Length: 202
Ligand SMILES: [Zn+2]
Image (cartoon, rainbow, N blue to C red; front, side, top):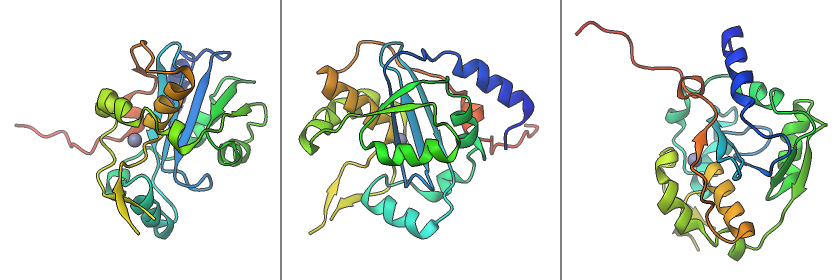
């Protein structure tokens, strides 16, 4: 769980979202056990992005091989309870656009956010991954957490799925290109991860 000071820091951070602007949301991992969560407002450029340690390591390993390619050891330092804290702090009656709403539905509903409405924009495999190369080429420095080799079931190597890149590239398909806004993280780096570097005299 988050400290009281962090919860107040989160609330002030969540204020940067426009409750009536177009907001994308995508997750990696199943809604009952998500490991990467991203929200994206292309108008203001704000984006929410954080990670979570998985509960089902067996399901995580299969999800890593065929989807996100995340090393589980990179998730040991994630802030616990951050998923519930961020979902609790989302603006009320917000409308969220997503590709595949039924799992975004399960996640938000498990946290009691029935006020949030979902727009299930569905796209082809061609349209959803249309700007995949352009988005990764432009924003690869926003997520270095996809270190494993991902294959698609014969098996051949594909580009790993990132919840943040998915939001950007799905919006790129609908809007027909990359948005000109400069992307800015809403969540502080020290709220997403807990520092593993001990204070040492040198
Ligand atoms: Zn990612």
